[PDB]
Image (cartoon, rainbow over all chains, first blue to last red; front, side):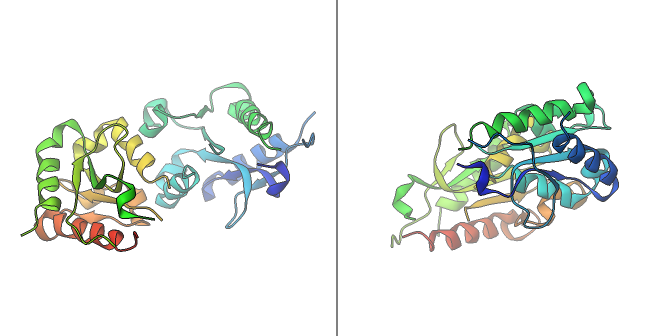
Length: 127
Length: 127
């Protein structure tokens, strides 16, 4: 409804193993070379509210059952949930993602460009 | 909000392989040996509205990527979604179900008793 309703624009949900990759994505989204301001990014925390939620789906993310639960909680209620798939084969991708929007990590800037564009698209709908 | 708002009480979501098992569950829920009436059951169809949705999770259900998508759509918005797991080992169960409610098919009446009780529990909250 409004961009100023939530204190953050993007959230990066990741497993303990992909801490470095998640930090690089946060610095990519905020770091650029009717509110007309820059992207306000953060690393996903408990009770942290943001407009868009980026799920950094990696082999380590799928191995952890809690990350798979958090993925289902993010997709529950329209909305902004951007699943980014890096470091794994397309055959190993969760089969649910066939019928929904996802960003492949084999694209430009390791999929960081397409996720940033997806965030920017959603922010236009607000206020 | 009201039991009379939706034309059905239960819905049984299943893959093409488990048609017989889904029909047996429908006949179990409706067949009994502030509305105080019997359970109105149906086999899950496109645009079919009901209070509770029973996901008949079997090896065939997990093999089909569409059934896994429909499981995510059912868990999206509180609510009544009863996943029933039959014909598969506990190690083969989807890891998301660790942190949420599910009914094991190894229990009384093949898990049909616990799913019926879960439906009856939810119907008390309505009107």
